[PDB]
Amino acid sequence: HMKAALATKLLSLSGVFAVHKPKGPTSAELLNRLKEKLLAEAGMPSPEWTKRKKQTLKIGHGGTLDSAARGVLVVGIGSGTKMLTSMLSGSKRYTAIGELGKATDTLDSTGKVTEEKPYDKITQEDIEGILQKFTGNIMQVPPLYSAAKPARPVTVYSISLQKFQPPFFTLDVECGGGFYIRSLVSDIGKELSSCANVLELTRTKQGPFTLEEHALPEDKWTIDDIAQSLEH
Ligand SMILES: [Br-]
Ligand SMILES: [Br-]
């Protein structure tokens, strides 16, 4: 089962690439599934079964993506794990769906409802209007259940409203690393004299890696595909 030439190839890879994380798994669980998958392809033993030799695969991610979210997760392999600290400086892009009228303790659709306000007076123009208060250098309080927290300075490069089907508004956001999309959605609901929480959250870009162009689907989580897409 061991394929020695493929094993050499796997352990020779070093750089950064991106994968597509589906909704459901944590970022740690996805890294574990990806690590076990590549080792099994080469026929190498599990990490709990390595002989403490140099033939130990090194892998990690460069910016966490929560369980309920989807999209780009940056992965470092080989000595490329030493590059991941610098990957945090890159800007991010999200597509988020907020739901007016309902607030939750987690600020998304997984938590428990904490508040209900009407939203029938909110028009699409009303939303487009207050988006500029959230564009540029803004103050933002992090979500309570994130790791309350003190307000922190964050950067929003662009926000656009793609769709409004009350109560659901879909936002396209280009922002800095430390920006919280859940905070933005909750505050947009407040600023419109209502409330809101995140129904769906897709990270479409982190740094130089976009979901549209770079993110490897699961069927391409192979030694050869990763080699071809690696950024040394
Ligand atoms: Br930021
Ligand atoms: Br968030």
Image (cartoon, grey):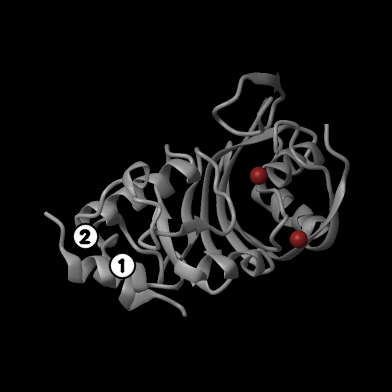
Which quadrant does the N terminus fall into?
A: bottom left
| Quadrant in which residue 160 is drawn | bottom right
Can residue 208 be seen here? The reply is yes
Mark 2 is surrounded, within 10 Å at the Cα level, by few (under 14), some (14 to 19) or many (20 or more) other residues, namely many
Closer to the camera, 64 or 143? 64
Which of marks 2 and 1 precedes in the sequence? Answer: 1
Which amino acid type corresponds to the residue marked 1 in the rendered image?
Leu
Which amino acid type corresponds to the residue marked 2 in the rendered image?
Ala
Q: Which x, y percent locates residue 152?
A: 86, 50
Which residue is outermost to the bottom? Answer: 232
Q: Which residue in the structure is indicated by mark 2?
A: 42
Ligand 2 falls in quadrant: top right
| Quadrant in which residue 155 is drawn | bottom right
**Residue at horizontal 54 percent and vertical 28 percent from the top:** 110
Q: Which x, y percent locates residue 40?
A: 23, 51
Tell me the SS state at disc 2.
helix
Q: Which residue in the structure is indicated by mark 1?
A: 10
Q: Is residue 92 left or right of residue 121?
A: left
Tell me the SS state at disc 1.
helix
Can residue 206 be seen here? The reply is no
Mark 1 is surrounded, within 10 Å at the Cα level, by few (under 14), some (14 to 19) or many (20 or more) other residues, namely many
**Residue at horizontal 28 percent and vertical 54 percent from the top:** 39
Q: Are marks 1 and 2 in contact (CB under 8 Å)?
A: yes
**Residue at horizontal 49 percent and vertical 46 percent from the top:** 27
